[PDB]
Image (cartoon, rainbow over all chains, first blue to last red; front, top):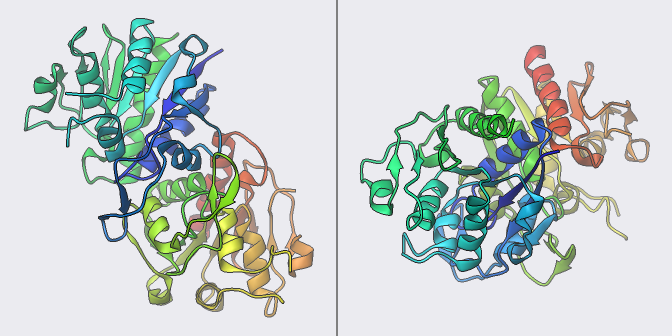
Length: 213
Length: 210
């Protein structure tokens, strides 16, 4: 009987969660008969972005209200998460994850998020992270672990600087840190096709599920 | 092969159904069909807080919100060149009915001309039109005057001027005569993978047809 938490940061790749990554994470959890629950913090987004003009705008949106779009309404305040009810955690990417849960691209990490991910980590429960999310996971774990992830290619040495180890990985595959139970894939870190992005997410969720079995 | 995709916003209660739109795009890509997304440049009729599930007093633009689903690559539907496409798919979402039509309003029957005209162009050119969830009901209504088409919405199509064929979430329906293709998706509270299975069948049918 398998359950996964999914943490969302809004609804959109420029100010929230990457919508395709979130949908594909939920599709593959469901393909594996893993039930899930979505969580988000009840806070304003750092920015709202017009995704057609690709410009920030003077309008305000709540991360949890917007995440309810992706969740079709079934999204819960992250302060309400009971980690014992889940076997694993998946964090889709999107610029909002980095912008809304950290200052690491503006070291601070939104406490309710750090605490949630640390609770999964300290309970030895697999954590999956897509796109930029692996960088945020590395950073929030860096004082207690040096974890291994991919963000695709890291010519700038971001993961090393954040206190982890980077593994180069194609869009269609994923990376497993089998000591720290951290799983990752690169997805829209590259300007690749949706089908290839999906192949990588499919491998990540598979690997997490096989780990629990 | 090239497909148009029409979007009505970003969210199942006031725009396009996000899962349906993403899963349609995944299957087009799967079958190496290129696509372009289109939306009208007009405000949504409502903005719905998807957490409380109530309309709220905010104003959002259909095309700007559709750009979230399209990662930026969405174009004003008034610019659609139908001759550049082999087929059209319309994901569902309550926004497709509420933003493009008065058909589900409390109080004289009407469809947004730029949407009505684009879909008619496809039909009149003998090009497959695929529709998910509530969208087949809107397609039936907009063709009513020139055709009585067969669609599924799973288990109102009579009232709108069409003919309904029952279909499981995991399958799809084809009106071979009128080149209309449909699947039921979130018309039932079914699992996300089951909804996927029917969108997959629909797209595979449209592609296999061509």
